[PDB]
Image (cartoon, rainbow, N blue to C red):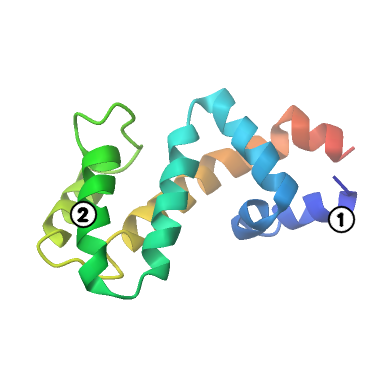
Amino acid sequence: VSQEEVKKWAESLENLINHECGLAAFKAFLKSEYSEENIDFWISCEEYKKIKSPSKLSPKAKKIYNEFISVQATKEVNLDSCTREETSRNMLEPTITCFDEAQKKIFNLMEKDSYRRFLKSRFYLDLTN
């Protein structure tokens, strides 16, 4: 990784997720915090943000909701108790802003924790001496 690219990670989370090596380094970093569910959830949420038809959101919404938001999900995602409940009510009316609020929580959570840790992480320090 070049020293120019890691500095972008210090400028915004999107750059870390939009960087080919940031994703590689970020995916491995999540493994350290066992927060790999966050990136898998982010990939499903990204597809949700690209679908602009509220008719197809329902089918996949139940699968993502039952898979990632289900209290019985084998891989529950770290979210507030209100965010999950809000998504459940959106199932009655699937909109493009249905999972947008949840992704924002993942962005703020990893940003308030992963970014703080990334700057102090050995990987960032090694790449950023």
Mark 1 or 2, nearer chain start:
1
The residue drawn where x is 69% and y is 38% is 25
The residue drawn where x is 43% and y is 36% is 37
Left or right of residue 71: residue 117:
right
Type of the residue with mark 1: Glu
Residue furthest to the bottom in view is 52
* x and y percentages locating residue 124 in the rendered image: 77, 37
| 47 lies above or below 35 | below
* x and y percentages locating residue 80 in the rendered image: 27, 43
Q: Quadrant of residue 12?
A: bottom right
The residue drawn where x is 20% and y is 61% is 58
Left or right of residue 23: residue 93:
left
Label 2 sits on residue: 87
| 113 lies above or below 14 | above
The residue drawn where x is 85% and y is 38% is 127
Label 1 sits on residue: 4
Instruction: Indicate the secondary structure of the residue bearing disc 1.
Output: helix
* x and y percentages locating residue 120 in the rendered image: 71, 34
